[PDB]
Image: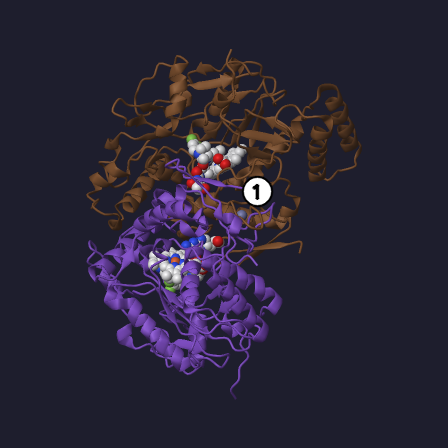
Chain colours: A brown, B purple
Amino acid sequence: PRFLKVKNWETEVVLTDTLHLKSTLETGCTEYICMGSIMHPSQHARRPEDVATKDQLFPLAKEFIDQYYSSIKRFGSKAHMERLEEVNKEIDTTSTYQLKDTELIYGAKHAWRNASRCVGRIQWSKLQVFDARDCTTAHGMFNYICNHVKYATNKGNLRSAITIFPQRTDGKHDFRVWNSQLIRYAGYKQPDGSTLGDPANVQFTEICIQQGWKPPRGRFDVLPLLLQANGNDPELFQIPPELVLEVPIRHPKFEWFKDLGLKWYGLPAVSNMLLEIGGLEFSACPFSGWYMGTEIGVRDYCDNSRYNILEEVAKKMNLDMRKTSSLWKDQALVEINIAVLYSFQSDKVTIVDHHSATESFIKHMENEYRCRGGCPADWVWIVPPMSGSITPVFHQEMLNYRLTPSFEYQPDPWNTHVWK
Amino acid sequence: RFLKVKNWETEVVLTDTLHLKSTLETGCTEYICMGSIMHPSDVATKDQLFPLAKEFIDQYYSSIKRFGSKAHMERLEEVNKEIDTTSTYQLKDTELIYGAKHAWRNASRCVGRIQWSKLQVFDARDCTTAHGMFNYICNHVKYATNKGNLRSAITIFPQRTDGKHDFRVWNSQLIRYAGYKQPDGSTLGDPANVQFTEICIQQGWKPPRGRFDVLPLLLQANGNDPELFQIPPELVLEVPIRHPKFEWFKDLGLKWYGLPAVSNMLLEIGGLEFSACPFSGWYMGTEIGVRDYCDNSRYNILEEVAKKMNLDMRKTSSLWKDQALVEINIAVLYSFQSDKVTIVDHHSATESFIKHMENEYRCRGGCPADWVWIVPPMSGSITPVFHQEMLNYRLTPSFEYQPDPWNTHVWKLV
Ligand code: HEM
Ligand code: HEM
Ligand SMILES: CCN(CC)CCc1cc(F)c(F)c(CCc2cc(C)cc(N)n2)c1
Ligand SMILES: CCN(CC)CCc1cc(F)c(F)c(CCc2cc(C)cc(N)n2)c1
Ligand SMILES: C[C@H](O)[C@H](O)[C@H]1CNc2nc(N)[nH]c(=O)c2N1
Ligand SMILES: C[C@H](O)[C@H](O)[C@H]1CNc2nc(N)[nH]c(=O)c2N1
Ligand SMILES: [Zn+2]
């Protein structure tokens, strides 16, 4: 039938999903095969890669404008029918169209709202949108990003924000932030074959060096920005450090902890994803919010191809690291995440633990099913990477489907950029 | 067609061709994923049974390099004779053992499948009464427990006939502790089991009304009223739960049974339905340490453990819950290993399953897997499966869920 129930097996709440009937693009799954643990399951875009014909772009534009005007209790109004014919002539005469300030804000907010993988979405409508569509150079991108960071950091009282550079036009004039996130630490391939800093960014850190960045070759070296405007070669910019809020990691009991010389930055800011609205593609749209403690303390510190400080922390803890069954990783993991939370909170840097976040997300689910007929959600990603079953989401059935507007992954620019 | 899955921690990339052999539905659509739905959702006619039988027989004779052979073709013919004359058919012992092993191998939710081929199959298809079932299961338990050196085993009771003569183990698992709701709303024992405990008590069981009462087997044979039987106490191997560092942990009075034995599922081989097929392995620690003890609607000992740990329970962000969950799980592992009862920690088990998965891709062309279930319920990202992409599809033979027998049985006595 035309309904799909999700059940929470810890509370027996059953929600009834009709919103999935609006899903537009494929999840990757078939009746015969589920792909819910595939990181990039589908390539079902809504258009061909480079500027699409009218009969391609306009149907997507019409659908979005239709949604925007429906959202605001119009549809068929004078302004809706005018906007349609304005988008028509704009596509006719430029092969694209330009979003209104209102529609741009609506779209950004809803792409966040539709981010199935985001546990933080209860905040979705409280997003600050910086319109950077007038930007024309990497210097201008740098100014816009600096302001983003300064506004978003707000001295630790972090604030959600997105800065939207111009939409893709022909595909050779992309605006891109080459950094995956606005603030990452460098990773250094060492002579022996080990790795100093953040191993995830070894490749990006080398592009930076290979572009003239002079690496301090330390553990927590903030990477420069590598900004690409209107398709041109990317340019390095050093973020003013007074804008990169950093928290030294200490522990509320293990005083030897701060002597591990660990710190992390306060602002998570995804800068390599693509924001899609009415078939328009915003290839540079850095968006930031605030950390769930597990992202630093479980993934950034404890993944094997990341900082991998589990080994160290357990040593100092005097744990039996002979076998796995002492749970020495699990014990050290918990202590590390206590430290991360405690440090952020002591410095009044906005952070949320995985209990509070997951609980917020269940509330948001309820809110969404009540007012929207559903809420797309990716269990594989919503469930935090430690203490899964002692959080409310583990026991929460989630329907996952693709609504638009949305954030999409996109090739890393260096796989695609022909240099000049 | 092919399909690739990536491990994002190691970058290993396996290629799945075996998904082509799936048929049963995942419940996902092309536009919705149901990968976190627990149950995404009565007797086959002759026409339905023919191709299901054929497919299984074909697959069995393929697995033993006798496809197209004379013995293969007579078997197919023999099966068809039965489905005509008797509207069903009877597995050979070879086929039953193979089918049971492959239902395990095909169990996408099971992290323990590296052991699938070492499965001790007990053919109980001659059983006719609940007493026979009691006997078969006692022997199952005694064999699988093996004084703490646990052995995988399944006991398979007569397949479904018309649906009106089903064999069922009414117990969800062979060994479970009873739960009793109190007038005041509190719960003694295992809160997950209060319903079944009521049913047993209703059937004449005199409960000791303690924290760790092993429930009685409630056995149904041939569609008759189920009957109560008390597992001989000396067959229930049990581990008192102590902690290697906290001398006070033993004062929690905690124990758990050593033998995990699922009895509420249905084994499907070649379209035949084995509604009673209890199977057993050994525990991953977190099944006891994270879920049995720490699920809020289970034994919920995080409160007590945290208190005796002095943890600050005012703010979640102290991670008292997290920190106490670990110590509970250390205790569970230490307790079993000390008593030389088989158990596997989540790290060892996920590691073995990655090697198994890779091997299954190598020799079989894939390994369906339910990431939502394969990832342990604690410390997920620090185990290799977390970073391992996985394809979920339904291969037959398979273990399937089935309705609880008290929601479908129509009673015979009085
Ligand atoms: C405000 C606090 C926020 C929190 C606590 C939060 C939390 C998270 C977490 C934990 C993830 C998974 C992270 C990972 O392991 O990679 C995630 C993913 C995501 N978030 Fe949020 N988020 C927040 C704000 C935002 C904002 C402001 C946006 C967009 C404007 C957003 C959009 C997304 C998207 C698109 C993903 C998917 C990323 C991917 O697929 O790689 N989030 N979020
Ligand atoms: C030998 C050691 C084994 C280990 C360590 C093991 C471990 C596990 C775990 C942790 C689960 C998840 C269950 C949950 O968390 O609720 C599971 C599920 C499952 N196991 Fe295994 N298992 C083992 C043996 C077996 C055997 C012998 C069979 C059958 C012959 C089997 C069939 C299954 C099935 C069908 C499921 C799915 C449960 C469901 O769909 O609800 N397993 N196993
Ligand atoms: C495949 C996943 N990988 C590759 C991109 C992610 C690695 C990574 C690196 C980061 F610096 C980082 F912040 C994240 C978390 C994303 C996030 C975004 C927002 C807006 C808020 C929040 N709290 N978290 C993930
Ligand atoms: C989905 C319903 N589940 C969770 C609510 C019931 C709880 C429960 C109770 C058990 F006694 C139990 F063994 C399991 C795990 C199943 C299993 C089977 C085998 C062969 C080995 C093993 N190690 N584990 C789950
Ligand atoms: C809602 C969700 O599907 C449900 O809690 C599942 C998640 N994954 C699981 N994984 C295992 N191993 N055991 C479980 O009981 C569950 N429960
Ligand atoms: C293979 C698996 O899909 C992959 O490791 C996913 C699992 N879930 C995740 N969940 C979050 N939040 N972030 C991640 O990077 C991942 N990785
Ligand atoms: Zn799916």
Near-viewer residue (B104 or A264): B104
On screen, residue B292 above or below A209: below
Q: Residue at x 48, y 48 (%)?
A: B18
> Can residue A246 be seen by looking at this rendering?
yes
Near-viewer residue (B141 or B237): B141
Q: Is residue A64 left or right of residue B396?
A: right
Q: Residue furthest bottom?
A: B414
Q: Residue furthest front?
A: B70
On screen, residue A321 above or below B80: above
Q: Residues within 10 Å of mark 1 (few under 14, many from 20)?
A: many
Residue A156 position in % (x across, y down): 42, 30
Near-viewer residue (B49 or B258): B49
Q: Residue at x 30, y 46 (%)?
A: A330
Quadrant hosting ligand 4: bottom left
Residue underneath mark 1: A27
> Can residue A386 be seen by looking at this rendering?
no
> Which image quadrant: the N terminus of chain B?
top right
Residue A83 position in % (x across, y down): 75, 29
Element class at badge 1? loop
Amino acid marked by disc 1: Thr
Q: Is residue B272 left or right of residue B354?
A: right
Residue A278 position in % (x across, y down): 66, 31
Q: Quadrant for residue B137, please give it.
A: bottom left
Is ligand 7 within 8 Å of the beta carbon of the residue shown at mark 1?
A: yes
- Counting every numbered tag in the picture gives 1
Q: Is residue B185 left or right of residue A122?
A: left
Q: Chain of mark 1?
A: A
Near-viewer residue (A44 or A280): A44
On screen, residue A278 above or below B175: above
Residue A350 position in % (x across, y down): 43, 35
